[PDB]
Image (cartoon, rainbow, N blue to C red; front, side):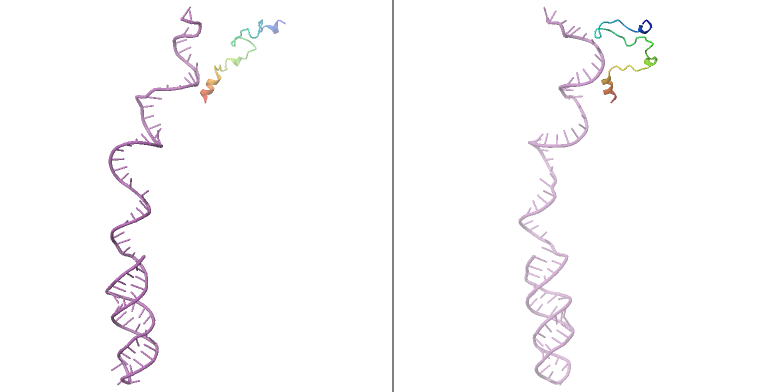
Length: 49
RNA sequence: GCCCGUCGCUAGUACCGAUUGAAUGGCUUAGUGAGGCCUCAGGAUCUGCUUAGAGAAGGGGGCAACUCCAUCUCAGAGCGGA
């Protein structure tokens, strides 16, 4: 139970918790850093047309 | 009073008009003005009835050419009509 439960957090509510997108994790892909971080969809969708 | 009121950004929402580039419509200025009508001329062209000249077929008479009129083609003088 120790080795399988290291990447977990002990929050209490799904709507009253906080998370980060840039957390360090071995389960995270190495190419996640090589991914585009697009801000807003509809603005660049209108821009690209 | 008073609260959600400044700052720059993400898109949207109404604007003005100092703006040009066209086009539409109505008043107005000046000039041009098609087409038909009526009217003044014009006369490509055609054509009817009189009267001149040249040719034929017919009959009557000098009986020998020649003469009288009868029926047609071309060219003139006309009056004309469209």
